Image (cartoon, grey):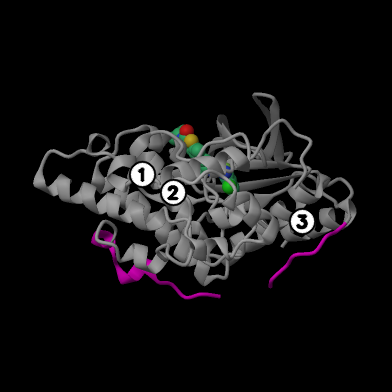
Amino acid sequence: DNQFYSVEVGDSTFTVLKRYQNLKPIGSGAQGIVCAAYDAVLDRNVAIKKLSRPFQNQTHAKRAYRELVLMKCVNHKNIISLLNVFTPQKTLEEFQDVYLVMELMDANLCQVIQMELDHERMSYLLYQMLCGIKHLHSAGIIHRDLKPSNIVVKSDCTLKILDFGLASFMMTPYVVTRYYRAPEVILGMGYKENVDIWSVGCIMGEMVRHKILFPGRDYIDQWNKVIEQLGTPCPEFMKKLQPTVRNYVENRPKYAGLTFPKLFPDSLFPADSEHNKLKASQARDLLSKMLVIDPAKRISVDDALQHPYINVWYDPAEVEAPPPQLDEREHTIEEWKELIYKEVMN
Ligand SMILES: Cc1sc(C(=O)NC2COC2)cc1-n1cc(NC(=O)Nc2c(F)cccc2Cl)cn1
């Protein structure tokens, strides 16, 4: 008789529509807790994400509102699409949580990165990330925070990006992962679409090396790892930095940088047959063109899709699609609560 029922999944209580049965924990990040469930109405398995009090603070509220609005806009096989959105609370006064429902995937890209992948699967996963980023860019969305935990895949190698990136203080224990951010984000520099190509390079490099390329406690250690491996950037890049940051960057020790065959040796690639030897040199070539500090010299998404390691998956039906407003204002808890509540109640 009650439209909703509640079940305990670890430390989180999930109050969901009775169509969703056999809820089980699968993962969790920071914005919310996630469960697998059987949807008895659609006769299919789904993933349910709980957003607890999204209006509680500016950081939570801006992301919750933006991702609800943008999700209804974008329509791409490599970008998340919601099956349902609901709240168990009946009024704005009582409104507390938002539940988002999507197709159930099998793993996040962090799990995939740990496995040895042949060139067929590695290049197909990179092709799909580039198709998804291309669709985001066509909709006027430049991501800037693409990372493995926000990318999901199924057993058949299909892939979907879960979030829309950057729009600051948080009193929670969870710290954000900054290892995939481009130099232009690390150094507050101004950016174009190919800021996301740096993140694809970091992901690709980690798939090969099975270790994060540019780790660090904060941007200080992270920038050191970038220059130690790729080398000190050109003076043309140095002239585009803001004066205070430019002084910091030009006063670090000078690094020549390691060659891409040295950063990614043949030992890390399946290099047995002539077919695989060519694919490994093509994979290194693409890494060489994405992991470029200066965005004026870094490869674009469209040119990355045309790279010989990627273009073996090209097809006009999914590379291109028909494109389609613009929100970014500060609000009180009450105003954010009503903006998110109105979006949940279409
Ligand atoms: C990372 C893993 S692991 C795994 C698994 O164990 N599958 C086996 C097969 O039966 C159990 C499934 C997934 N998976 C995660 C999502 N979605 C979100 O993380 N967020 C998310 C959401 F849920 C709902 C809406 C929005 C967002 Cl953004 C989808 N699939």
Residue 246 higher or lower than 314, as above or below: above
Q: Nearer the viewer, mark 1 or mark 3?
A: 1
Q: Nearer the viewer, residue 310 or 180?
A: 180
Q: Nearer the viewer, mark 2 or mark 3?
A: 2
Question: What secondary structure prevails in the magenta region?
Answer: loop
Q: Position of residue 178 (x, y in %)?
A: 59, 43
Q: Nearer the viewer, residue 265 or 334?
A: 265
Q: Is residue 58 left or right of residue 214?
A: right
**SS at mark 2?**
loop
Find out whether residue 324 is within the magenta segment.
Answer: yes
Q: Amino acid at mark 3?
A: Ile
Q: Quadrant of the C terminus?
A: bottom right
Q: Quadrant of the N terminus?
A: top right
- Who's the residue at 41% across and 47% down the image? 256
The CA distance from mark 2 to mark 1 is 7 Å
In the picture of the structure, the residue carrying the numbered disc 2 is 231
The reply to whether residue 108 is visible in this rendering is no
Q: Which residues are magenta?
A: 311-331
Q: Residues within 10 Å of mark 1 (few under 14, many from 20)?
A: some
In the picture of the structure, the residue carrying the numbered disc 1 is 258
The CA distance from mark 2 to mark 3 is 45 Å
In the picture of the structure, the residue carrying the numbered disc 3 is 340
- Who's the residue at 73% across and 67% down the image? 327
Q: Position of residue 244 (x, y in %)?
A: 70, 55
Q: Amino acid at mark 2?
A: Gly
